[PDB]
Length: 52
Ligand SMILES: [Zn+2]
Ligand SMILES: [Zn+2]
Image (cartoon, rainbow, N blue to C red; front, side, top):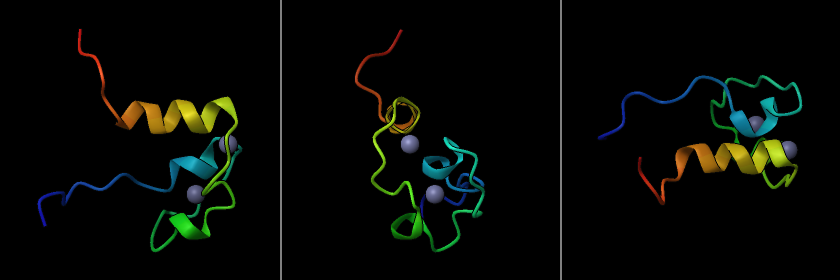
């Protein structure tokens, strides 16, 4: 693996106040597909389209 530094807990569900540890989760994230502006802002934090 080239990413041994995984993020703690799932961020999709913390947006609402969830903490599952993201261990074998994602599909288990009640927010796995949420769309609120805190779940989109999250996926946005990881993706990078412009640098400053
Ligand atoms: Zn989650
Ligand atoms: Zn959300």
